Image (cartoon, rainbow over all chains, first blue to last red):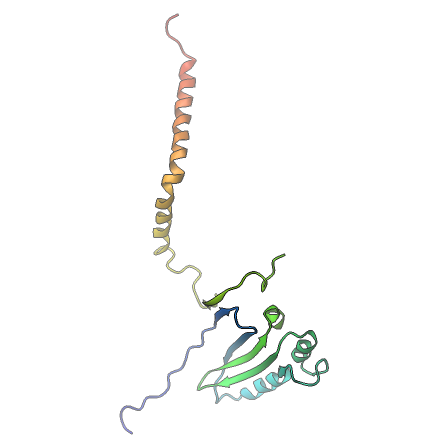
Length: 112
Length: 75
């Protein structure tokens, strides 16, 4: 031990966009998130509950129209995606909270 | 017509952007700003300016000839 043992410095969350346009690939991938609090924070539980309500979807799920989650349900009936998943990624004092989806070029807007 | 998603084919182009709430609306406004307007001016004077002075001149001469004409010495 002794000298040469540093801690972790906080990481500024920015909030921006990176778009890698590539019309050669057949389905678009999009990932959007706000800054979450870190591992320690008590409120990761309420976030996970809300995320669960939104849930996830995939084109192989049985139950389309009748799924509880309105996103899932509207996505299945209107065929707005191939898959989507909410997430709550945790790091020291920060995190990414949001969702990721995969869809046809003409469905990115409705999906968002 | 038109729409988005049916415009044209684009590949291999990344676009980094930043939220409007994280950047300034007027970065080097006077610093980079004024040099640019001077540069834009240089680029265009020789194409915009001349026609106009030709009129400016034709205007002042045209007025002088007219007013000086309604006067007369002998005969």
